[PDB]
Image: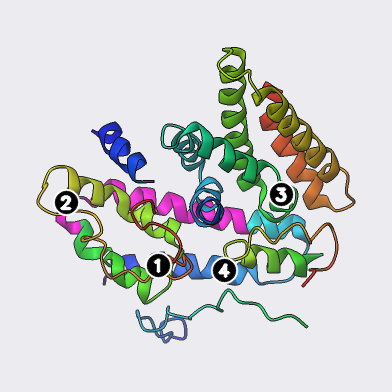
Amino acid sequence: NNVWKIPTGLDKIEQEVKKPEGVYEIIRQWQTLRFLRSRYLFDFDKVNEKTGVD
Amino acid sequence: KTSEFISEKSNVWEDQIKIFLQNCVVPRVLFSPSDALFSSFFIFMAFRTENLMSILNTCITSNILKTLLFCCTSSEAGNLGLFFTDVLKKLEKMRLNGDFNDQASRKLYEWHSVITEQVIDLLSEKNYMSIRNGIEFMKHVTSVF
Amino acid sequence: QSAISEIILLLYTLNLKANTQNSHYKILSTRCDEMNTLLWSFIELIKHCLKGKAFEENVLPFVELNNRFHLSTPWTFHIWRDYLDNQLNSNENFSIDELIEGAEFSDVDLTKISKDLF
């Protein structure tokens, strides 16, 4: 009964994502890079195995 | 029919040379292999020699390969490796066909040196991701080097 | 019970939440890639079995996919390119930029680029 009480519908899968823009203050760098690969690719030389140079 | 289309389209057409790589060929290549092969084939047979050389020079240099091979997953690295194998095989066949001799010698050797430096640099890092990525990418590209 | 669109959207938006977890990278990369391959294979099955009008009936048409849910453009085209090419080739009545009209193309920034080339 529990697993059949879960609400299923098109209105619930929307779960809108986070906008590409990321504000400026080894997995965290990986995630931030995966997310920024689309917007600002050519500003990538600054990474160089270090903290994200903003 | 498609080549007829691409004829007029090429009659039609750095900022564009930047955004093209940014939102059109890099997203397409990191997909399944067929998308990579197709980005390779469409890079040629769709542009003039001048603009083509400029685009390839803007992609090879500017130090994008090093990090972009850190970010992506394993299979995405394999796909990008297939794309570089295809583009370099075609470039080397074009060279060994003597068509490009005037100044393409120096520029081609500069490209080879810059790619060698980038791979040699990325292949030397402490993380596990960079090592596995570099290994897969070279396992694809070393066939024609 | 019309599960097709719900399942595709679920698989996609699940791989993202899998991307935002915390663990050893040696398992994170493999998990993300495994989910990606599963979604690709599911869509290959769907395109293999549902053809003609049943596809356009139960596969959530393009503009909604790209404007309401904000799918990344490569997946959108990976679904719709075969059907668009079929409707374009035989029925030469319609034309591209019309059968895909209205799409916001959100991450693209269509400024400073010819939509023809895109």
x, y percent for residue C94? 14, 54
Mark nearer the viewer, 4 or 1: 1
Q: Chain of mark 3?
A: B
Q: CA distance from mark 4 to mark 2?
A: 31 Å
Q: Amino acid at mark 3?
A: Ser
The crowd level at tag 3 (other Cα within 10 Å; few <14, some 14-19, many 20+) is some
Which circle's residue, 4 or 2, is located before the other in the chain?
Answer: 4
The crowd level at tag 1 (other Cα within 10 Å; few <14, some 14-19, many 20+) is some
The residue beneath circle 4 is C16
Q: Name the image quarter holding the C terminus of chain B.
A: top right
Q: CA distance from mark 3 to mark 2?
A: 47 Å
The stretch of residues the image draws in magenta is: C32-54
Q: Amino acid at mark 2?
A: Gly
Describe the element under mark 3 as helix, strand or loop: loop
The residue beneath circle 2 is C52
Identify which residue is drawn at 15% across, 56% down: C53
Which circle's residue, 4 or 1, is located before the other in the chain?
Answer: 4
